[PDB]
Amino acid sequence: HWGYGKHNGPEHWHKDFPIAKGERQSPVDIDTHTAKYDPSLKPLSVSYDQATSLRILNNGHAFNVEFDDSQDKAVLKGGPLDGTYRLIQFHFHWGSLDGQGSEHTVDKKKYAAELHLVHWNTKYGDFGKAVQQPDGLAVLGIFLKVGSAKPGLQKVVDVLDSIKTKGKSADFTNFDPRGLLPESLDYWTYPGSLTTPPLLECVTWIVLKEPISVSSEQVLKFRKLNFNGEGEPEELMVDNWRPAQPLKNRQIKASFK
Ligand SMILES: Cc1ccn(O)c(=O)c1
Ligand SMILES: [Zn+2]
């Protein structure tokens, strides 16, 4: 099955998931010079004050911090979006070295990691019906650079040793995702896809311009997780990023001058 190694990595995924070579695949390189300012975009609204985290899961590709999405609680709206999108989970993609790890790139620059806050369009009722639609998801992408620690990340980092291997989960209540956001909500946006199989083309991407800083010790702890299950040969969970895909017939719009 799919993964990020030599025999099952991104260059193989098209055989099981032909949409890998589709018309609106993600991630992409964001050419900042050619991303046009769009004065019709609204400011983004991130309303996370009532977010209810439940659990943290090592799914064998990343760790997901899961939310109760059964009520109207942690929503993204405004910006490029029509309607209301509800937070379901976040996770990260990261590198084996600080010089790589992000999926989107900015003028070919790779950041050390990328945070994805995944939301589904509430007009479709739940996540599973939303991934059957071209406007079913909105993913808020936030770059991570290595420098100062992010204090709001530390509760996540401390729980990782309890979910080292694939299939492990842990209770993870009362985590506030507002502590992972940068000061500015200036963003780029374009239509694209999930960046892991099943690679579905559902996503309005909203990628913030301002990265957050995490410490080298925080990202080192991400790199101690495992892609394998307990009792299987240890393969460190590193380099779980897909490289940039062809832009094709798409425009990237900027919310800022
Ligand atoms: C639903 C989904 C699956 C994989 N990734 O990376 C995402 O950002 C979102
Ligand atoms: Zn992701």
Image (cartoon, grey):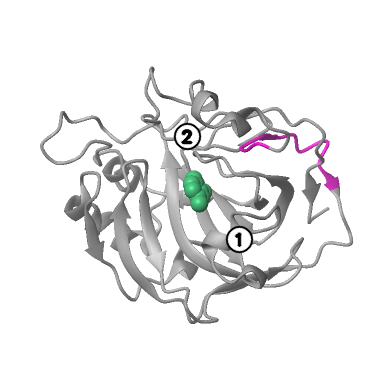
Q: Which amino acid does the dot numbered 1 rest on? A: Ala
Pinpoint residue 239: horizontal percent, then vertical percent. 40, 31
Q: Quadrant of the N terminus?
A: top left
> At x 55% / y 81%, what residue is drawn?
72
Q: Which residue is under mark 1?
A: 130
| Residue 241: assigned label | 2
Q: Main secondary structure of the magenta part?
A: loop
Residue 85, image quadrant: bottom right
Residue 93, image quadrant: top left
Pinpoint residue 233: horizontal percent, then vertical percent. 15, 28
Measured along the vertical axis of the image, is residue 33 above or below residue 200? Answer: above
Query: Disc count in the image?
Result: 2
> At x 74% / y 47%, what residue is drawn?
190
Q: Which amino acid does the dot numbered 2 rest on? A: Trp
| Residue 51: assigned label | none
User: Closest to the observer: 71 or 73?
Assistant: 71
Pinpoint residue 255: horizontal percent, then vertical percent. 78, 56
Measured along the vertical axis of the image, is residue 198 above or below residue 14? Answer: below
Pinpoint residue 227: horizontal percent, then vertical percent. 28, 37
The residue at the far top in this view is 6
From the viewer's perspective, is 196 left or right of 140? left
> At x 73% / y 50%, what residue is drawn?
189
Q: Which residues are magenta?
A: 25-36
> At x 24% / y 29%, what residue is drawn?
235
* Residue 31 is a magenta residue: yes
The answer to whether any part of residue 115 appears in the image is: no
Contact, CB < 8 Å: mark 1 with mark 2? no
